[PDB]
Image (tube, rainbow over all chains, first blue to last red; front, side):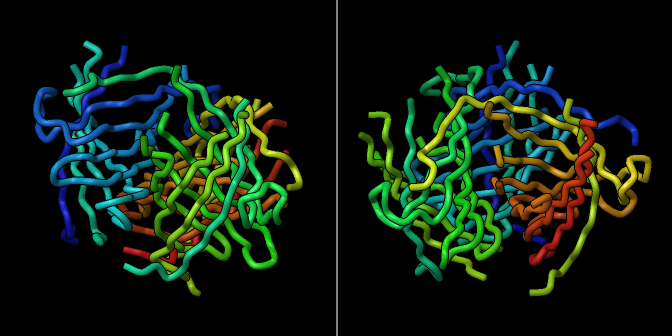
Length: 128
Length: 128
Length: 128
């Protein structure tokens, strides 16, 4: 399938059978990260990535791109676990310009420092 | 677009570039709140709002309207971050009567006390 | 409606008006559980169930089936609260083979020990 809309953003984060069933107590890390048009942190910011993930002693990720720029106004929410420096995550929600949008995002992670840059390539397959 | 179904509920909660990337440890607050047809807490209850949000030292919200009334039987789930006394949040899931439903909700907050009344105006744009 | 695709999996977990508005601090339990084709833990594993739930002192559940088998390659994510030994939960996300899929799952719980087997019956009503 070809997507009815493609978007690319970067956001910047600073840290600080077979196997049996496995549980543990979790701790939540909450983040609020700048989203930029290109790779550099000092390139134009177009919103904030806000969400959370988990440490055990944690493939789980929930976050929203809160977009607020001259061309993009809305939110896109993603949720799920995926264990490669690259993973897919489902679009799970949309508001504003991204009202009723659906699709997937490919997340590529440049790890450096406590500095992580995440390339997020959004392919929408339903667009309103 | 005009919604194929509109619903209005209130639920009642009782408490107790630019910026750099920002993380912290989070704490979860879980809530289980009555949903009513109208503004007053003592008006007919039609279900419970059950979910969680986060304190840092937190625009993130995940919750489900568990509806159980003479006219509404099902669940509606919402998730996302939005930083106005009014915000939008995406429908992310539905069961029962709201099976395969999609759309957005506008949330208006009356803050008082530790008492918060939230007006939730659901506009579905896909209805089964 | 008849589903365009039906799937059945089991996963195995090992523990260890009216009512006023109710909140509390929550603690998160994270789990990573084997998914099998049939009831027995020693039957073929087809992936891992990875997500979290909450203890108060908690009908909330978020998890992803990370499927990795000879016939199924993708993820399916579910989220929501539902208070019966059986409950429904909405599909909220999909990737890979389950890209753009939507529907509901019925979850049946066999409680034993700290051992819980969950029968998950997925009915997709949108398939790509």
